[PDB]
Image (cartoon, coloured by chain):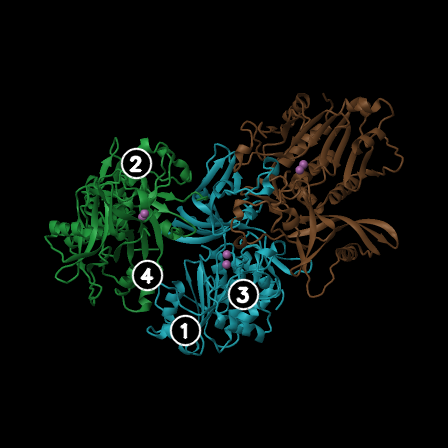
Chain colours: A cyan, B brown, C green
Amino acid sequence: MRAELNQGLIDFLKASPTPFHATASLARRLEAAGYRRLDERDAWHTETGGRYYVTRNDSSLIAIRLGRRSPLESGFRLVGAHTDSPCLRVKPNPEIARNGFLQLGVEVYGGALFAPWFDRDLSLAGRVTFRANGKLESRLVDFRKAIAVIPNLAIHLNRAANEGWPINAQNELPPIIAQLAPGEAADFRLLLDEQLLREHGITADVVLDYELSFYDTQSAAVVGLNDEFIAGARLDNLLSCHAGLEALLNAEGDENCILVCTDHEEVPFLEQVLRRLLPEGDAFSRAIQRSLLVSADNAHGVHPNYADRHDANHGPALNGGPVIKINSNQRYATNSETAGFFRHLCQDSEVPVQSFVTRSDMQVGVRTVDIGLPTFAMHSIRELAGSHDLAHLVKVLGAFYASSELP
Amino acid sequence: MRAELNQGLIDFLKASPTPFHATASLARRLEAAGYRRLDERDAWHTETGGRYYVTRNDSSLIAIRLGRRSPLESGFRLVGAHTDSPCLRVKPNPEIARNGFLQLGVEVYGGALFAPWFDRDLSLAGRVTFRANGKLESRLVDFRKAIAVIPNLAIHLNRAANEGWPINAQNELPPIIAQLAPGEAADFRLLLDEQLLREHGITADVVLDYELSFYDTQSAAVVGLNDEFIAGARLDNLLSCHAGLEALLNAEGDENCILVCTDHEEVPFLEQVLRRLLPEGDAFSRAIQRSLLVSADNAHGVHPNYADRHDANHGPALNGGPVIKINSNQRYATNSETAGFFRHLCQDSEVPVQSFVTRSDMASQVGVRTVDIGLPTFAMHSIRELAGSHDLAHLVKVLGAFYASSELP
Amino acid sequence: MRAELNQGLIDFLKASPTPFHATASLARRLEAAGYRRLDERDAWHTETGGRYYVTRNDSSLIAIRLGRRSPLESGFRLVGAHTDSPCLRVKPNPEIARNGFLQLGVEVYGGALFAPWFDRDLSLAGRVTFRANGKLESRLVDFRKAIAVIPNLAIHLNRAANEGWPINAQNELPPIIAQLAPGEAADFRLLLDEQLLREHGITADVVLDYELSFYDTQSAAVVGLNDEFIAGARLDNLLSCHAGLEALLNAEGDENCILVCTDHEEVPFLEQVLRRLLPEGDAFSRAIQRSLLVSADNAHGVHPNYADRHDANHGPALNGGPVIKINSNQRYATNSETAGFFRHLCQDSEVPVQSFVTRSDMQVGVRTVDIGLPTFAMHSIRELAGSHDLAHLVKVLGAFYASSELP
Ligand SMILES: [Co+2]
Ligand SMILES: [Co+2]
Ligand SMILES: [Co+2]
Ligand SMILES: [Co+2]
Ligand SMILES: [Co+2]
Ligand SMILES: [Co+2]
């Protein structure tokens, strides 16, 4: 499955600098495959089998592939991922004007590593809400061009730099985007208004608020002497989003399938959607108890320069295939029946499979196995995974999507 | 008018991932412009009006533009830059095999900022020395392709990462280039040999040693909402090398002109070369006292997230022109005469000029008077530094006015 | 307006020293306004145009305005606030007898500031559960009188008192209520029986258990040279409770409206009440997705003596109007659409509006905007707010309640 798959990933990451864009990319692909969009606000006709997707807040998406069999007999085959990643968001009154520069004050979304955000050609994307012709409207904008940089302080002026210092997100992370007069006027909402005309043709009476993420304009790429790796932003968790979608779109059979890609993992929807798919009563409970959730989120590869952060018996290899993640304290829902099932699936697909627990010194109600492709450096602005692993994961999710029996 | 310089700089940086490659790029352009190479091993016949360059270790270059009058009478105009930048160099027995990976051990060259080298698509380039059927060869290689990465450790396994930790070069900086295990012979010198075949159609008997730097494969680029900035590796100090060379090739007037770009600044050539110009005896000392060296190396612009690392009266602006660097404890050789001269020179060429002095709580065995100047930058010694998209034009104009200058102090 | 609104607030705080008392004060206001209590054990018949309220544990209240067009088309407009505040609670067996004094052991409720509770004329109020003719009753009591003091230790005996010491809640916070003889014997439940007789004309067989809060007997008050401020206990969050009830009672139009004042916010109901207001499980998601929750809870005004605790670009000003609270990491669920709407709603209702974000180094599935009035000294026994802001908040909350169209 190539190469083609790895190229599909790179394009998908490119089109998705935010959870909003991620969602839009998933939906345009779902639509090209003939899934019809449902609006939660409207009444649903619903025809049995039955290809649908629904969004919430333009940043969460559920894909529903209804099969021949009653979900009360066959249960659901659910794959879960998330559409968000740690990053830096623009503040509501962002303009900072000092030493000739115009900067934008940012907050740190999620458990982001600060250091890798320095010295990158960053751009800006996300959702803008504005008033046009009286009505409230929302669009996505993506500046595409590299408009921003968080420069490092020179080592000459910070000689114990490599000894480590607590990077202060308030002081040290606002990006520079331009130079000002001064005195010159600076209106970031005016800049967004320009970007609305430019990107959308819309003229806008005033710009109200926004959810804008800086991101790396350097694309994901295949790296390594023998091309054994993929480097890029947002692998956690768009690698899983892409994988599950590719598995859903190419799945054999007529099983009841769901793809759930939710927002804010990194900080109800599925339940309300499912309760609408089912004639209420014991139907919900009977379908869900026959179901299985494969929760796909990146795993930690044992890192060669940091090998002792891992249990020696449980250090996943990049390109060694999907990792089954166990944690007895319910950090992962995986148990012997869901783990045993997934393990059996990989064997029948001839896909290699690994295990991970952490070092011991470190709500729908569905059965769940937690898996993930091994990865280095989450959540940096540029994470690392293996170039063989996407084909592995797509193979077994596709096998799972086509599985008649579940535990 | 300004954008071709910047385009040329981006091209120059791309072709120069190492000091060896920068010297090669500089030399290629000089030859295209009519400068001819002198070998230091050989006798020189230098006629006036002549255009020469000189090379040492394939990583230092001196470019000579001999003028109408003897340098004994009218002096030298000298611009200095350097061809090296902090980076990671491959060790001589580099193969590290563990957890299924192949890695290359690296030493840190210069005062590199470690953290920015993480999570970068790295490639490998430099000089390779080998024995071929059966003589001693040196060639330059550039894998071009992204072959290596130094991944960060996940924050889940280093939760107090943003509080800082002392990054250990021996431990945390060896890059991953491939996967091994279940076997398997890993021999780096053999990989170099395939790279010799692939790049030069050359095969080798045995590869002996090599000087190879890892570099960022992401090109330099113009950035900012109004394109005010240039980002890239090696702005320290290929920015000045470019600037100096553009200015040398296009400067008007006669006048004796010198471009000196030396290696190992980040850690005798010039003096020996200048002496082989001019007659024996007192000719040298007399020429040098009528001479002036503009040492061009990047300055620090005042950083708006770190503004108090600067003196509030001496905070250079990106795109505010060349900076005169003063340190009366001779960290810079600038004195009031050479600073005065350069200031006069900028004012005549309509080029804006700034001053820098360090916060007070923080050549030349030739004996040439010197002014130290630089274009203001951020993130000096990072894998990716920042500079003004306007400053290069500013610098080339004033160096051009310097090379054309009739009089010196 | 304003002076009358502020007097109403003051009276409300006085009437409400506990969650139980806040709920009772809300309940008797609504009933005066014609709202009829719905018992959760009963079956409900709700007509259009209905005005209802329902309580739980006598300390949470949900008031409901049913309009004419169905929640399936128009959704609900919901205002959220909470009934509780940080304070000190009497323990089950509280009598401490030492040094001639009677004291009551107290546990610290919520994230209270300890120092301000010292040297205050405290009283005691809350719920008493007792047995009367073997029947088992609960009544509210309010001693009203200043019956307790937690005195500071004199600076002469604690000379570095101004250097700060860790205040130990178990040791330094039990208040003094009386003096005791040599061996005089004290029974707190006996004093509670006398208060039952005193306040309700009731004798108890035996007093069983209780939930009693100490509170300051100093009334809320307008303060400042130009009367720009209001000072009082429990401004977090009875300020919002009061503002929401005014807004609900005076709201024009006939749209579907909810006021949610819950208990225990400072350490299920809403969903269960909403589900009983509309048929299927398809109707729930449809109506909730068309709804909007303005979650109203005090924000932090930038304090002139601690101004560096705020972001310089996001320092809300007392009497500056409601504050839209923002946090990408969902400490506040505000997004660009619900912020846009609220900002619009303020600007075309002529109320000034402010944004808040923290310094970067510091459910039922409904869209939400977190907003609050700017406040000083939050979780102290005596908090500070603007004497102009309550009028602002009531104005825009009413504007909200009369909004036909929601994001
Ligand atoms: Co994840
Ligand atoms: Co993550
Ligand atoms: Co330098
Ligand atoms: Co340097
Ligand atoms: Co509160
Ligand atoms: Co509170």
Using residue A217 as the reference point, say whether residue B217 is left or right of it: right
Element under disc 4: helix
Question: Considering only order in the chain, which callout, 3 or 1, is on the residue closer to the N terminus?
Answer: 3
Q: What's the amino acid at mark 3? A: Ala
Q: Are marks 1 and 2 on the same chain?
A: no
Q: Are marks 1 and 4 on the same chain?
A: no
Which residue is label 4 attached to? C288
- Of C269 and C320, nearer the camera is C269
Which residue is label 2 attached to? C153
**For discs 1 and 3, the disc positioned in front in the rendered view:** 1
Q: What subunit carries mark 4? A: C
Q: Position of residue B107 (x, y in %)?
A: 69, 46
Which residue is label 1 attached to? A289
How far, Cα to Cα, is label 2 from label 3?
66 Å
How far, Cα to Cα, is label 4 from label 3?
32 Å
Residue in view at x 35 percent, y 65 percent: A42
Q: What subunit carries mark 1? A: A
- Of A343 and A56, nearer the camera is A343
Using residue C340 as the reference point, say whether residue C251 is left or right of it: left
How far, Cα to Cα, is label 1 from label 4?
26 Å
Which residue is label 3 attached to? A243
Q: Residues within 10 Å of mark 2 (few under 14, many from 20)?
A: few
Task: Tell me which corner region of the image, top left, top right, bottom left or bottom right, holds residue A6.
Answer: bottom right
Q: What's the amino acid at mark 1? A: Gln
Element under disc 1: loop
Quadrant of the rendered image holding ligand 4: top right
Q: What subunit carries mark 3? A: A
Question: Considering only order in the chain, which callout, 2 or 4, is on the residue closer to the N terminus?
Answer: 2
Residue farthest along the left direction in this orientation: C201
